[PDB]
Amino acid sequence: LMAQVFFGPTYYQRLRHMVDDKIHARARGPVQVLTRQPVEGRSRDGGLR
Amino acid sequence: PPQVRPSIAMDETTQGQDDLTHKLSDILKANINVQKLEMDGSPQHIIN
RNA sequence: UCUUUUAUCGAGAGGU
Image (cartoon, rainbow over all chains, first blue to last red; front, side):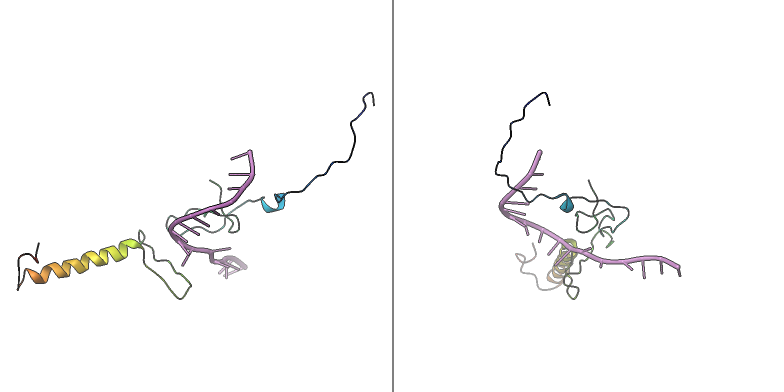
């Protein structure tokens, strides 16, 4: 390469935000009772606002 | 109609009532109370 | 030939 690269070991740490805990989608799940609209939640096949 | 006042089921074997049910019930209690006093014994300052 | 259930109110800790 026509350019040199700064190189060395650094101390990295890994957080608690994972894509496997955020992906979500819905087709036709449950509804509420008061307004018969989609519900609020992710662990309940909820809908987005 | 109770489509507006739904009753939740709590621990499946317990169920409370939405506020408007208890409030209508209290208004009706106060109605049956207001009847009697001005139909017989009336100390005036118990009616108003 | 299907279908198939997730309380409620409130409080807090968080992510852009």
